[PDB]
Image (cartoon, grey):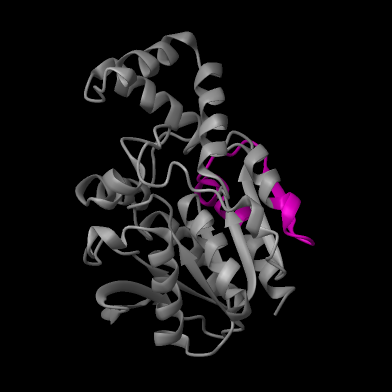
Amino acid sequence: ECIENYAKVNGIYIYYKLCKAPEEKAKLMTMHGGPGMSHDYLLSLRDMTKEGITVLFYDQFGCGRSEEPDQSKFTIDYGVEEAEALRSKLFGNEKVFLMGSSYGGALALAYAVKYQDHLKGLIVSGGLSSVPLTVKEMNRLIDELPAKYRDAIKKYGSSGSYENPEYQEAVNYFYHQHLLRSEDWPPEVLKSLEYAERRNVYRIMNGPNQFTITGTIKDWDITDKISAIKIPTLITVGEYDEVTPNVARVIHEKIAGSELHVFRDCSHLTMWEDREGYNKLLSDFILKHL
């Protein structure tokens, strides 16, 4: 069982789930994607506790269970501080491993740019260093989609009508091809997608759905800066990932000594499509850089 709490972190009460390992050997901190989802769809990473790796889960500002701060704080810069303040308020000065998924990845990268001296290693899963690139690549994916669902996305999408069934059917298809390649989606994932649809962070910082990043981060891009990350980096990405492995290449290209693993037959949520494979990779990487 994990130790849950609702303590104050950098101003607003933030929820976090710390799952300690019987024989802890390294503490890994996680950053869920979104922006505006939750730690829920990352719970599968708990398996690493049986490898001497304590995993700290938490809902970023305005997400899941945590309270929503002032809209002026709906930025990655704020997210970083929140991440830092949480790492110290819990572990103090101890060096830990940072991981992020999608937005959590881009976020994680930003954190590394200013707080890499507080991390033993960095893990980026289906993350990004440039939202624009992610958009250019995501548009290519939609075009490759079968004309049917493709036309729907562009038609109703431009008419600002994401409530239409034809549009949703396409959104569902796309998701079932680049978000999670399985039917019978795990609850944890559906729980996260529900949290982002109830809160506000997703509507402001991101936008409507996945392939529609028209929020307040659509122009974010720290590519010409991530090159400053020196700590060991494990960059993962699915073969059919909504955040194409090409984007993962841009991040890999800068960070020297960084690894780049492309999970075949997997999409964006590889931690669920290959729970054992994903958990093993991160556990190995971490343990090899204690």
Return the residue nearer the eye: 58 or 11: 11
Residue stretch rendered in magenta on the structure:
252-278
- Up/down of 13 relative to 270, above or below: below
Where's residue 47, x and y in %? 52, 66
Return the residue nearer the eye: 52 or 179: 179
Q: Is residue 261 in the magenta section?
A: yes
Q: Tell me if residue 223 can be seen.
A: yes
The quarter of the picture where the N terminus appears is bottom left
On the picture, is 14 further left or further right than 289?
left
Return the residue nearer the eye: 20 or 152: 152
Quadrant in which residue 76 is drawn: bottom left
Where's residue 241, x and y in %? 56, 37
Residue at the spot 70% in from the left edge and 71% down from the top edge: 231
Q: Is residue 241 in the magenta section?
A: no
Residue at the spot 38% in from the left edge and 60% down from the top edge: 39
Where's residue 38, x and y in %? 34, 57
The quarter of the picture where the C terminus appears is bottom right
Where's residue 154, x and y in %? 39, 16
Residue at the spot 68% in from the left edge and 66% down from the top edge: 229
On the picture, is 90 further left or further right than 187?
right
Q: How many discs appear? A: 0
Q: Residue furthest bottom?
A: 93
- Up/down of 287 relative to 105, above or below: below
Residue at the spot 37% in from the left edge and 51% down from the top edge: 35
Q: Tell me if residue 279 can be seen.
A: no
